[PDB]
């Protein structure tokens, strides 16, 4: 049957890849699009735990697809899927820097809104 490309890891119907190179959020998204995917969306605790345990691993902070670029304080996934699940750090999102793109950081995989021009690794989903 159909499989992920080499170096993409399968999970619950989709393929996942850590992009190690540090880029801005938009640059990370463009790289995912070039590979036929998009930035990671996370729709369940089970998918979050796969991400932190197998994809992110020791990497401390990376971009995912959540963002409020279009409408402040209304976060959406760049890939167009529904926001059915969130895992924010306490008091995030806080739109501190005047922050419209979302990172995962820390061992529990909780999320933070960050300046989009920060260079960080990312995760694509396919
Ligand atoms: C006070 O705000 C928190 O700490 C800052 C260093 C930033 O990482 C910011 O995104 C985060 O929400
Ligand atoms: Ca914002
Ligand atoms: Ca923040």
Image: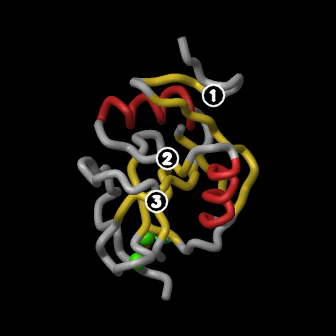
Some atom of ligand 2 lies within 8 Å of the CB belonging to the residue at label 3: no
**Residue at point 49% right, 51% down?**
105
Name the residue tied to disc 1: 8
Task: Return the residue nearer the eye: 29 or 100.
Answer: 29
Q: Is mark 3 on a helix, strand or loop?
A: loop
Q: Residue 78 carries which label?
A: 3
**Residue at point 38% right, 44% down?**
42
Name the residue tied to disc 2: 40
> Which residue in the rendered view is the most extreme toward the bottom?
98
Q: Is residue 68 above or below residue 33?
A: below
Q: Is residue 96 above or below residue 111?
A: below
Q: Position of residue 109 (x, y in %)?
A: 43, 43
Some atom of ligand 1 lies within 8 Å of the CB belonging to the residue at label 1: no
**Residue at point 35% right, 79% down?**
71
Q: Position of residue 83 (x, y in %)?
A: 28, 54
The disc, 1 or 2, on the residue closer to the chain's N-terminal end is 1
> Which residue in the rendered view is the most extreme toward the right?
21
Query: Are the residues tagged 1 and 2 within 8 Å (C-beta)?
Result: no
How far apart are the alpha carbons under marks 1 and 2?
Answer: 13 Å
Q: What element carries label 1?
A: loop
Q: Nearer the viewer, mark 3 or mark 2?
A: 3
């Amino acid at each position: 049957a159909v499989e992920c490309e080499p170096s993409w890891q399968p999970f619950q119907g989709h393929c996942y890849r850590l992009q190690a190179e540090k880029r801005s959020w938009q640059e990370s998204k463009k790289m995912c699009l070039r590979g036929g995917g998009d930035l990671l969306s996370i729709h369940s605790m089970a998918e979050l735990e796969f991400i932190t345990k197998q994809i992110k691993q020791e990497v401390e902070e990376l971009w995912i697809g959540l963002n409020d670029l279009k409408l402040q304080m209304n976060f959406e996934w760049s890939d167009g899927s529904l926001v059915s699940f969130t895992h924010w750090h306490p008091f995030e999102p806080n739109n501190f820097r005047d922050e419209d793109c979302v990172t995962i950081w820390g061992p529990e995989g909780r999320w933070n809104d960050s300046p989009c021009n920060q260079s960080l690794p990312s995760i694509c989903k396919k």
